[PDB]
Image (cartoon, coloured by chain):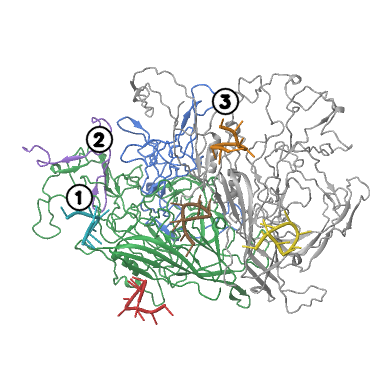
Chain colours: B green, C blue, F purple, G red, H brown, I yellow, J cyan, K orange
Amino acid sequence: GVGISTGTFNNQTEFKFLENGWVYITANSSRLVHLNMPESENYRRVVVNNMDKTAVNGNMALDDIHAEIVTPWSLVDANAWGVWFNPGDWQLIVNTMSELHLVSFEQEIFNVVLKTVSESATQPPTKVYNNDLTASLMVALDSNNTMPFTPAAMRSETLGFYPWKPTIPTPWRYYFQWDRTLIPSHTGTSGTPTNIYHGTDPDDVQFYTIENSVPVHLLRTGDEFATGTFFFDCKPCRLTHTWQTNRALGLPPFLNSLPQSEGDTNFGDIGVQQDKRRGVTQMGNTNYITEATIMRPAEVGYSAPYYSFEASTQGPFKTPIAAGRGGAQTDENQAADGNPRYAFGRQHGQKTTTTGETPERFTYIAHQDTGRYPEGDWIQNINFNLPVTNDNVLLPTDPIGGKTGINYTNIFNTYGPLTALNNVPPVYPNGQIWDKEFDTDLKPRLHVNAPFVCQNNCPGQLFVKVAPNLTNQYDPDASANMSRIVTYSDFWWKGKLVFKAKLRASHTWNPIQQMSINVDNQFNYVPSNIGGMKIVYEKSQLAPRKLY
Amino acid sequence: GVGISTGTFNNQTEFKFLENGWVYITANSSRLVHLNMPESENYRRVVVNNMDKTAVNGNMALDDIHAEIVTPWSLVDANAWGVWFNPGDWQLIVNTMSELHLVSFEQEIFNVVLKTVSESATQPPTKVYNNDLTASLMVALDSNNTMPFTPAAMRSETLGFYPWKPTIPTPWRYYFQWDRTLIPSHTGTSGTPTNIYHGTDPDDVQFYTIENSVPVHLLRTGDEFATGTFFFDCKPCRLTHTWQTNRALGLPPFLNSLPQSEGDTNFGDIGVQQDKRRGVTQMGNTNYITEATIMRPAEVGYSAPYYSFEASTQGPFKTPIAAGRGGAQTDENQAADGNPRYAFGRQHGQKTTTTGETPERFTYIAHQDTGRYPEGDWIQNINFNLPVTNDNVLLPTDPIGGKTGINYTNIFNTYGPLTALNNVPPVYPNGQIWDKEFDTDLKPRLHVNAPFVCQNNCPGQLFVKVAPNLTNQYDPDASANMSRIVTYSDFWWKGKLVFKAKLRASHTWNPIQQMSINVDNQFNYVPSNIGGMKIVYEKSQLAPRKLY
Amino acid sequence: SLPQSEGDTNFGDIGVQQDKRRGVTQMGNTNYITEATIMRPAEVGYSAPYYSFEASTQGPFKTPIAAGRGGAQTDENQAADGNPRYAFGRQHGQKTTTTGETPERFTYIAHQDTGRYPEGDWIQNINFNLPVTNDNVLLPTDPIGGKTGINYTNIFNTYGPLTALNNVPPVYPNGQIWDKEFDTDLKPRLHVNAP
Amino acid sequence: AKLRASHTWNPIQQMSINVDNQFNYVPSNIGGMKIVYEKSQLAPRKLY
Amino acid sequence: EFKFLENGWVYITANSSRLVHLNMPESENYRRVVVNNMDKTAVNGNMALDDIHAEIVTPWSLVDANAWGVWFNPGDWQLIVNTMSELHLVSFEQEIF
Amino acid sequence: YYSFEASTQGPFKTPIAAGRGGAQTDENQAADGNPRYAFGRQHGQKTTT
DNA sequence: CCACCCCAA
DNA sequence: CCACCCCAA
DNA sequence: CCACCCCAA
DNA sequence: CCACCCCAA
DNA sequence: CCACCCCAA
């Protein structure tokens, strides 16, 4: 064994150009992972109670109460964009390609090393590192996805985005059924509202164990653990955005009058009065045919309650939203159309030569315009009879429930069997790749965290742990937890992710928005005199498309 | 693994004599290379600004401003003559052979050893060296020459020329687009001329990475990395020099009068006046047919500006020249005909038992005479009507631009579609072997650094690095750069370079200039009582040939 | 020596004196190895006379040039590296809703840098012995022929069998596509009007 | 022609539509057209 | 038309069908004409303004399509420029109807 | 033109491969290096000379 | 896996 | 088990 | 040598 | 019975 | 002689 290599390193991005604008994208990410000895070799059940934040009777979205069980097992997640590509590759797929497709996935672990630490208390004292060539590593595959699913992208507990940079798995943990009650309360709400931790419903007690449910492969130094090739059965992702609303659909009016001189100030007037125009409307009252009135085939996107913090048996939680932009990013509401927010640090973006424990983030703002400006709507009477009168129109400005800050926009849900929609684009790096699917008879149309949602089972989680190294004293009949040899192990991980996508043709006349290097970009994609690295976020879908 | 050998040592020079004066020269150089742990495991971008030398307003050729990026990767170069032959072998190829041809090239690495250093702070303190048999070496081949090309001969960062002497690879580095401006200025030029470091043109930003672009082979102790056999498609090199100018071409005059007694003082006179001689001239004015006047089929070599420091977007740089000698090495200008200059130290010549940081060098002066004595030219009027008059002739002595030191010789470029030329001979040892070729639609006729310039792709660079050995503490989310185990590794490198050349026949009567051992050479090719070694430079092409 | 802190102001110094550096130069006089001195395999582009209006039996005509850019387009000479100039009207660019007989044009400035800043060269004595002295260096500023405006840069031709070159890129729209070839035994390496 | 692959890490200079381009590639209320000149070779390469 | 082949190879076939108009030639005779602008080349300053040449006019009207602007639009170019590395010229065929 | 170079053997004129240029009434029979030929009796020239 | 100072009894 | 800045002489 | 919370695509 | 400074296109 | 914004159901 312990004499020779087990694998090879490959962090290459291969572009296999096929026939009919079809390409083969096989991304390989061979990172060297380090891992320490688990604190406890015992499973824990821990309750988090931050009922010191949920008492101010102002703060209710700061509820951090949950019940989780810790596992001595250390997980490994590679479900991210930043791990599979660099700023150079992405630009290619984004500028050159139209739509992308996910294919294969196979993980491989090699060149396992396990070293023991000897603390020679002499003066300094000093530390002597050695090799326990008989030591082991405990590998586990949940090939039968028997266990919960913890995508470690959500909390930037992924793998390093810089290959030449050694990374670390994430200590595994999952949810245990915690029951609670918490009633809202503003600054004024007198007395203590209501908030408690019931405990646990004996029905919903799922206590998992990797040792019991999943085999463990005891690797040494001269052993290689490799997966297979995982074929993916999920829907394509489109590298295109829709810029069409409801006012940019169909046959525009006929302009009986056109300018005769230049300037975007000289407007071509139709030349007919609104209550004598031909065409179709979805009204039986009026005779006014307007760009706002006319009947359009359907509705793009929807309008839902914003900052609508619902709640159930586990506690309050915000209401998701799958909306593009809508309104020039100078007129948002980065809320209404729920724009993601990403917080990472040092190992998944951010300047490597930084300091402190303060993340950096960005509020990714797509290109697609299905989103809304809930500050330019209105609900009026069936009689129309405008110019509408106050008592005959409920606007954004007009409070609802007597309170100021509130709206009908805030409480509004316009989602009809006529709602048209586009899935959540990739958010690279940071962003997630693929995400399991709910086991509910009825399933969400699309997820908000990943462009891909697998239709069948997805790759099984790779759980990586260190095997207990024991001393000459060990009494299994002791209250305390024995004393083991301070062991750690570093191993090389490799990845092969396969994507298949199409090439974009030109059909307009006007060039399309591409990705480039400005005089303001340059030093965003290059190391610094000290070796300061960081990966910036960049828009995915930047290329027009027709919605109708 | 770790029990047995992986390779063998061979530093033998094989001469396979074939049929028709054809020989097979297979040089093998198996050197044992040592390599330390890279400072930083991060890539750097560093700017060099020596704007303390370029201010004296005298010194403009001392511009050392460039932008380079450091790579944790340590390179290995063997593109030299001294590594493949010894003073004994060369003499053979030089004295016996006519023309030489480059064939195969294959590298092989074996008997990898990785040791950790334990610093036992106790009294001295003391150092304890051990073996980390599970450690690794990261090998890389740029078989797809995706990366820049850094021939490490230029700066004598090659490999040792003495086989029984352990050597060291060169820390890899390459150029990053640096923009600058610098205007000349003599001792007098008042005020501060102009000189700045613009920065970087966002267009020309190439940030390479070996991990990303090239696979890495993780070698242990019981692993062998070997290349293939690289076939070379470059032009032959001639072990012959041309001694013919323009005055030694064709049918000399007929000497109507010959001496009748001895002495090189008794000259045989033609016996006809210059303005009544038969033959051809390239003049329509005169009737004077002279050895200087007569029409010769073409022109040997050319005459270019000397110490013509041009400049572009990166900064000033001297103008190359490919000229033999011209004038007895007692009358040079070691400038006009640009004679190379070589600076090495201890590991590539020079007396091993030397001290200090002061190179030794030599100004290699070929045998071929295509070079010029720009101190015996002249430009005169179309009327000729000599004896030429001042106002009718611009000579070397006559200043141009009003300044003394300057000439028309200094600013002169006589390169016509009639210029005949001979490539730059091998400069052994030191000198380079083969050099990639520019990727420009139009390409240089010949290089000034190497006899061989490959027509297609050349061998890929061999990048040798040490794998990060990590301790029990490592936080990838730290501003500082972790702490690794002080690891180094020594490995044996072997080389097989293949050459095919022809044998020289005798055709004159007078012996040809050969290489020998004088009473002044002897102790230039033998170790000393202490073991002082050094390799001297020696002329390549020493054997006549006809130019016409 | 490498910096230990950030900033493009903190430069990493080599740490060796110029007249004691190892490597190769194309000089037999000096011992100074500099980024300007060191021997490079060849020369990129060339340096020719600029606004060198020759003439023959048909009449005077300017001297072509096939050079990229060289120097940040903030430091040109749109002459030295002969940048094309294009004049069209209404049917080959230009705003259709225009008037008069006055073309519109552009001076296409490539990306490739083979071009030169002929305002940062110099020709000095074989002795080097710098800091160079006036009488020992002919610079751009220094007139040639007694006239001011003139240079040696203006009359200079550095084109050696070592000159590396890249052909003239497409200039779209306007620009030409393909162009016949001269019927001369000897032919131009590349044209300046067509890729 | 051939397709370009990515080999660096830093994105390459591409052609795009700015807020200053837009109306350089579209007819006008009257039908005013014109075609601007644009750089050809905008992508690095190695000379050595 | 962009015909994507195998091994990053593409086929670019540009078609430009323009409607040409043409008037009756002035003269149905060939001419030989000399241009002498020796009113510009006298100021003894202006020598690059020499517009003297000898040309012969043909009643025949030519047709040139040797340009980039005729074969592509700002949309197509951007593609070839952003997506492709090196370009190669192949066929050329003209048709009048 | 009339650029007499030199090397190790001695000075020698610089060749030129140029046609004519300018009406042979405006030459420089030098600039465009026009050949010059000198023979006698057995390769031209009047035999009865 | 040792042959006549190389490849190569 | 090195070919023309990727897969892939 | 990863398929739909086990053996077992 | 003339081929690339020998035998020997 | 109309198929999913090109060649090309």
Task: State if disc 3 and disc 2 touch (CB < 8 Å).
Answer: no
**SS state under label 1:** loop
User: Is residue C194 rendered to the left or right of residue B17?
Assistant: right
Residue type at mark 1 is Gly
Residue located beneath label 3 in the image? D32
User: Marks 1/3: CA distance?
Assistant: 72 Å
Q: Pinpoint the chain carrying mark 3.
A: D
Distance in Å between CA atoms under marks 1 and 2: 27 Å
How packed mark 2 is, by other alpha carbons closer than 10 Å (few <14, some 14-19, many 20 or more), is some
Q: The residue under label 3 is which amino acid type? A: Gly
Chain hosting mark 2: F
- The type of residue carrying mark 2 is Asn
The residue singled out by tag 2 in the image is F28
Q: Which residue is mark 1?
A: B250
Q: Please tell me which residue lies in front, B82 or J5.
A: J5
Tags 1 and 2 touching, CB below 8 Å: no
Name the residue furthest left. F48
Callouts 1 and 3 in the same chain: no
